[PDB]
Image (tube, coloured by chain):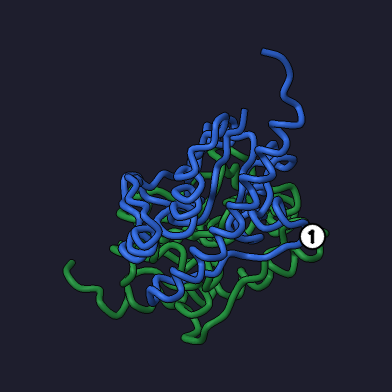
Chain colours: A green, B blue
Amino acid sequence: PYRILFVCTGNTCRSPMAAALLENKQLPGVEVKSAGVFAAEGSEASVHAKMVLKEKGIEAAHRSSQLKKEHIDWATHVLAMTSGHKDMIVERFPEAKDKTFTLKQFVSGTDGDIADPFGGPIEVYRAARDELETLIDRLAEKLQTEQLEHHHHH
Amino acid sequence: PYRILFVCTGNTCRSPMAAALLENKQLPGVEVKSAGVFAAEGSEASVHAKMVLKEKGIEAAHRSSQLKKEHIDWATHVLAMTSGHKDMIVERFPEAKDKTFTLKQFVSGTDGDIADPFGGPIEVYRAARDELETLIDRLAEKLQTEQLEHHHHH
């Protein structure tokens, strides 16, 4: 059972898009949340994030969350948008070091950041969305391959 | 009256040193706190921070605090250790924009970050302390000059 936690700073732009894209796939045995390292409670996803998600048929009704101990304990995998987020999470919650990765490194094996679209025009959000969708597709394939490989019982 | 809030990330290293240096002066009409953008509650200042403070005769109690709305509303001035911290504070708490500065910009008019030890050797903690001592001396002079200039009546 996977519990995937996507993390950025404000939990209004990158991580809600990552979460919405993964949740949209409705993968069995996968649960999805997002949170921000420094975020308000109950804020909507930003308007450009909502718009570019709508282009893909997604209307997630996101509400922002501050990243807390409870989320860290819940997660099987904490997938940070950038190496800076990863570093902050591990410093704040050292007990999470074994399960905290950047999204790019977890799915590709190679270090990389998802660029922050905040403050940018819609095409900058669409670029972030496209990068995220590719990574989430690869993530989905990774998880399901593992699930199938280790499936037993009847 | 002045309510000075020093801010870093973990509130164990730079901001507690800043707070301790200013509090040690016991300036009339000045209250001092510190908090961290992403910090645990109740942690001691780090050992090297305590050591370099001890070298200057300071052995103050510190308990780490997560930066919250309440600290922002309390402060007359939010003095960040770095521009990165300033930017995070203003993005998270837009209502704080007029009163949030880096310590360097507030006392010198140019910008700069306080040296980051990265939990490293005592020598870098000492370098940070020395930078802070210089800036906090200037801060003291700035506040007291204002207080004296606008002092009226018995």
Q: Is residue A33 left or right of residue B42?
A: right
Identify the subunit bearing mark 1. A
Return the residue found at the far left. A153
Q: From the viewer's perspective, is residue A92 above or below residue B94?
A: below
Return the residue found at the far front. B154
Q: Amino acid at mark 1?
A: Gly
Question: Which quarter of the rendering shows the C terminus of chain A?
Answer: bottom left
Disc tally is 1
Residue drawn at the location 37% of the way across and 52% of the way down? B58
Question: Which quarter of the rendering shows the N terminus of chain A?
Answer: bottom left
Reading the image, the residue beneath label 1 is A120
Residue drawn at the location 66% of the way across and 70% of the way down? A115
Q: Is residue A76 left or right of residue A65?
A: left
Residue A134 on image: x %, y %: 61, 75
Q: Nearer the viewer, residue B58 or B102?
A: B58
Residue drawn at the location 62% of the way across and 71% of the way down? A114
Q: Check disc 1: other Cα within 10 Å, few if <14, some if 14-19, many if 20+.
A: few
Q: Is residue A97 visible?
A: yes
Q: Nearer the viewer, residue A88 or B152?
A: B152
Residue B112 on image: x %, y %: 68, 65
Residue B93 on image: x %, y %: 64, 41
Residue B107 on image: x %, y %: 70, 52
Q: From the viewer's perspective, is residue A97 above or below residue B93?
A: below
Helix, strand or loop at label 1? It is loop
Residue drawn at the location 46% of the way across and 76% of the way down? A141
Q: Is residue A61 left or right of residue A29?
A: right
Q: Quadrant of residue A63?
A: top right
Q: Is residue A4 left or right of residue A12?
A: left
